[PDB]
Image (cartoon, rainbow, N blue to C red; front, side, top):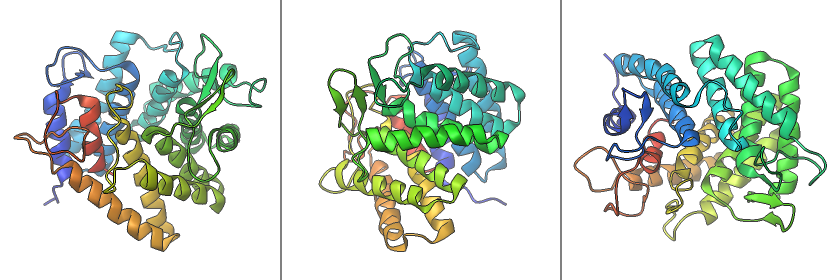
Length: 340
C-alpha cells in the first residue's frame, strides 16, 4: 500500500505534456516545437528532484530518479559538459546548484565535479570588491551590474557544497555573498532589489524568484550556522512577498509576459517550502507559520481552480481560463506547489 498525492498526478501530467524522451529535455510549450531555455531547464531539473523526494509512489519515484540523470545527459548532449562559455553567470550558477542537488540524490561523482567546477569558476573569477564593495557580476562578458539572480543562488549553491563537502570554505563563501547581498541588495526589511548598476546604482524592483532565492539562502544559512538572525531575515522576506507580490485577494502575481519571470513562482514556492519546513521543525514564529501555511494552501488551491480537461494549469493563479498556450515554465509552479 502507498498514499497517492496530487503532486504525483501533477508531475506525471507535466511530463506527459512537456517531456521529450528523445532529446532528454523539456519542450518549451505544449506545441512541442522548441526545447526549453538553458537556465530554465535547470529549474525543471530541480522540479523533478523535488517530485522525487515528495512522492510515496515507488514506481513514479524510480521513474523520476532515472529522469534526473536524463535531464543532465540531454542538456550535455546539446550544450556540452563545460558551461563556462556562457556569458551569463546566473545561467551557470543555476546548473551548478542543480548539479549539487543531483549529487546529494545519486552520489554520482560527475555531478559533484560539475557543481564544484562551475561554482568555483563564478565565485573565484566573478566576485569583485572594486564595485559596491563585493558581489558577483551578472555577466562574465561585461561588468556593468551585480544582480540578485546570481548572488543569492550562488549563496544557495555554496550551502549545498558545504553540506556535501563539509569544507568551511563554502560556508565562508555563502556567508560572504549573503551578507553583501542583504546589505547592498535589500532594504533590510524583507524587500530584495533586482540589481545594483555601476551607472544608476540600486534598482529596487522586487520579483518572485529573487525573494525566493534570498529566503532559501537565508534558511540554509540558519541551518548551517544556527544563527536565528538568518531565519528572521527569511521570515521578513516571506512577509514582504505575501504583502506586496500578490493581488488584492492575496494570490501571487502573474509575472508575464516576461519569459524569464513567467515561471518565477516555481523558484519561490520551492524556497517557501524550505522555510515552511524549518518553522515546522523548530516551532519558531508559531503565529506567522499558521497564517503562512494558510496563505500557501490558498494559493495552491487557486492555482488549481483553473478550468482544463487535463491536469495542467497555467501561471495565472487568479484566473480560471487560459490566455494563450500552456508552457512548461509557467505551468511548473503549480506542480512545484504540490511537491514541497
